[PDB]
Structures are given as C-alpha cells and as structure tokens.
Image (tube, rainbow, N blue to C red):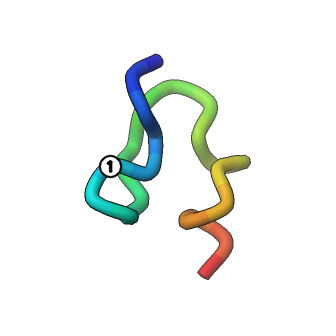
Amino acid sequence: HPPCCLYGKCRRYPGCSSASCCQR
C-alpha cells in the first residue's frame, strides 16, 4: 500500500483497518 494516513487521515487501502489514524 501507499501511505495509509495521507493528509493525516484514514483511507481504505488493503489492510489499513490497523492503521492508527483509523483507530480515532
């Protein structure tokens, strides 16, 4: 995947349900 927190914020690339901007 690219950066999952792009612009700080939580975009839906494959397996970024465990990015940290996604936790909120």
Q: In this view, does 18 lie to the left or right of 10?
A: right
Residue name at image x 72 percent, y 48 percent: 18
Identity of the residue furthest to the top in this view: 1
Identify the image quadrant of residue 15: top right
Rendering coords of residue 10 (x, y %): 42, 59
Q: Is residue 21 left or right of residue 10?
A: right
Disc tally is: 1
Label 1 amino acid? Leu
Identity of the residue furthest to the right in this view: 18
Position above or below: 2 against 24:
above
Rendering coords of residue 11 (x, y %): 36, 49
Q: Is residue 11 left or right of residue 1?
A: left
Q: Write down the residue under mark 1.
A: 6
Rendering coords of residue 8 (x, y %): 38, 64
Residue sitting nearer the eye, 17 or 9: 9
Position above or below: 9 against 14:
below
Mark 1 neighbour class, 10 Å CA radius: few under 14, some 14 to 19, many 20 or more:
few
In what quadrant of the picture does the C terminus appear?
Answer: bottom right
